[PDB]
């Protein structure tokens, strides 16, 4: 019953061959297999992977009943290499059968899958609720997760309302500290690269609408390539749809990967950057959110995107990523001229490598517990308390101190005597059921405390008062983990 690392993919291949949708995933695993195997052996030599319980894990892919398919494939691969006993489900019948047999210790599921879980198991679905890890790309903020609070704020979305611990939501990028970051793995260079080759990001013609001036400025200094036909200028060199090795060859050859504004926060810009490409990242001013952008309306989050790829913008930056105003002709020309003169430096954040994803998912499996049976994680030693100004979120004040909001610490910040420790003295206090508390009015020294523990929230700025904010440190290249979290 102890987990043993796997160094051979034969059994995995056999399991994924049972569902047609895994076909192009198996190809990707074969291409990446040597990287995965070096990674699990390297992790096991560097960190104690001994004496882990082998878990029976349900993976229910609601969406099989894309970036999402890449994330599923990397999660399943990581679980397999770490030695866990994986039961894959892509039907209501498999789901019923796996849960029928009992002994399930951990459940990875998507939003569509979760509705199927509740319907198929009936009222005892809640018995398993603490074992759920819900793959949810764009994230779920606490305000939308709390069904009754969402109704009371007049949100009309069908999404959210699961009443989970919001750290059970697993995101594509570390954009929502209320949630956990799952992510995925990103699959002489002077000689290989065509210095004046740009490639447009966007496999559909619709994405190209109103980018003519932008594309013309790039075309002044570079060839414009595409992999896509009304909106496409005559000078564009279309290679058609590519795949695997061919696309990787094209990226290896490309100096500049050109964002058009859509799609939002995909894997492709990280793949370009890993291959030595610079990424021209459209800036969004004002930021795009469920409040101003049709695509985002109904998403169970108010999170604002400052660019097409906020992760690339904030966690990578120049020289790999140039975040520019598409409508600023001077800034676009300067960016393109600078990129042309840049030395090529292929870059991959550690959190998007095989080893970094294995380390992250291994820490969540071993340490993240909503079922009440394990010591506090992250450990309390990691708490650094910060006061957010009015109009600033807990997410914002941690980030501006090179930290990350840690929602599991909110419970240690929620009464008069606990505040004393953090040089805040409450002359008076009350309880509110609000995402914006605990709060502090520094004028009249009035503290408002959280009356509904499900409403603790890294998201949300108080218009008038300071917020009392739980921050933690993170390992550079591994934002999901605090220094003492391994």
Image (cartoon, rainbow, N blue to C red):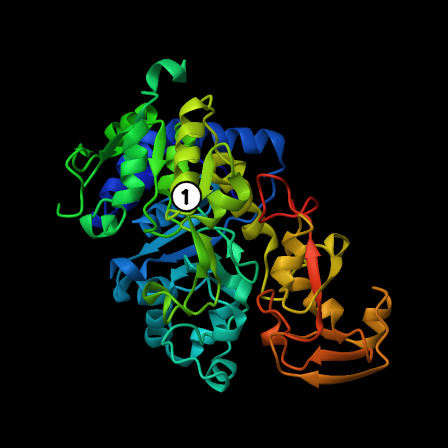
- Residue 163 visible in the displayed image: no
- Tell me: 366 left or right of 484: left
Camera-side residue of 55 and 283 = 283
Camera-side residue of 454 and 206 = 206
Camera-side residue of 145 and 313 = 313
Camera-side residue of 275 and 236 = 236
Quarter of the figure that contains the C terminus:
top right
Residue 443, above or below 196: below
Residue 471 at x, y percent in the picture: 69, 57
- What residue is shown with label 1? 281
Residue depicted at 61% across the width and 43% down the height: 51
For the image shown, how many numbered marks are present on the structure?
1
Residue depicted at 55% across the width and 41% down the height: 359
Residue depicted at 45% across the width and 48% down the height: 183
Residue 344, above or below 51: above
Residue 356 at x, y percent in the picture: 52, 38
- Tell me: 440 left or right of 250: right
- Residue 127 visible in the displayed image: yes
> Is label 1 in a helix, a strand or a loop?
strand
The picture quadrant where one finds residue 334 is top left
Residue 434 at x, y percent in the picture: 61, 79
Mark 1: few, some, or many residues within 10 Å (few <14, many ≥20)?
Answer: many
- Tell me: 116 left or right of 441: left
Residue 253 at x, y percent in the picture: 31, 23
Residue depicted at 58% across the width and 65% down the height: 370
The picture quadrant where one finds residue 335 is top left
Residue at the farthest front position:
330
């Amino acid at each position: 019953s102890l987990a043993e690392i796997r160094t051979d993919f034969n059994i995995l291949y056999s399991m994924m061959k049972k569902h047609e949708e895994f076909r192009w995933m198996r190809l990707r695993i074969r291409r990446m297999a040597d990287a995965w195997i070096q990674a699990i052996k390297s992790l096991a030599e560097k960190q104690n992977l001994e004496k882990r319980k082998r878990k029976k894990v349900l993976v229910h892919l609601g969406l099989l009943t894309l970036g999402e398919l890449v994330q599923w494939s990397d999660l399943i691969t990581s679980l397999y290499l770490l030695g866990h006993d994986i039961r894959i489900s892509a039907s209501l019948a498999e789901l019923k059968e796996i849960m029928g047999g009992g002994g399930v210790e951990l459940i990875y599921i998507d939003i569509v899958g979760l509705a199927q879980f509740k319907k198929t198991l009936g009222p005892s679905w809640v018995h398993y609720q603490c074992m759920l890890r819900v793959l949810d790309s764009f994230g779920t903020e606490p305000e939308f997760n709390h069904a009754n609070y969402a109704q009371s704020k007049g949100h009309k979305t069908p999404w959210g309302k699961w009443n989970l611990n919001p750290q059970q939501f697993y995101t594509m990028f570390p954009h929502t500290p209320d949630n956990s970051f799952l992510g995925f793995v990103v699959e002489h260079i002077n000689e290989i690269k065509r210095q004046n080759q740009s490639l447009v990001y966007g496999k559909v013609d619709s994405f190209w609408k109103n980018k003519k001036i932008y594309l013309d400025i790039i075309h002044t200094y570079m060839e414009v390539h595409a992999t896509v036909t009304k909106n496409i200028p005559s000078y564009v060199k279309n290679h058609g749809i590519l795949s695997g090795r061919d696309l990787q060859f094209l990226l290896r050859e490309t100096k500049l990967f050109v964002g058009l504004g859509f799609p939002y926060e995909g894997p492709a810009p990280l793949e370009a950057i890993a291959n030595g490409c610079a990424f021209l990242n459209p800036k969004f001013n004002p930021p795009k959110s469920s409040k101003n952008t049709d695509f985002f309306i109904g998403k169970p989050t108010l999170r604002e995107l400052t660019s097409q790829h906020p992760y690339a913008e904030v966690f990578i930056g120049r020289p790999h990523v140039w975040t520019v105003d598409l409508n600023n002709q001077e800034e676009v020309e300067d960016a393109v001229k600078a990129i042309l003169n840049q030395k090529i430096e292929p870059y991959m954040p550690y959190e998007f490598t095989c080893e970094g994803m294995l380390q992250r998912i291994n820490a969540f499996i071993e340490k993240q517990d909503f079922c009440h049976g394990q010591v506090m994680w992250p450990p309390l030693s990691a708490l650094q308390v910060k006061l957010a100004e009015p109009g600033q979120s807990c997410k914002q004040v941690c980030q501006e101190s090179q930290l990350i909001c840690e929602p599991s610490f909110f419970q240690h910040l929620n009464k008069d005597k606990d505040m004393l420790k953090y040089k805040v003295t409450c002359q008076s206090s009350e309880l509110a059921k609000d995402i914006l508390v605990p709060s502090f009015d520094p004028k009249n020294k009035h503290c408002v405390f959280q009356g509904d523990l499900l409403l603790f929230s890294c998201a949300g700025a108080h218009p008038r008062h300071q917020r009392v904010c739980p921050c933690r440190d993170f390992i550079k290249g591994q934002v999901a983990l605090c220094k003492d979290c391994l």
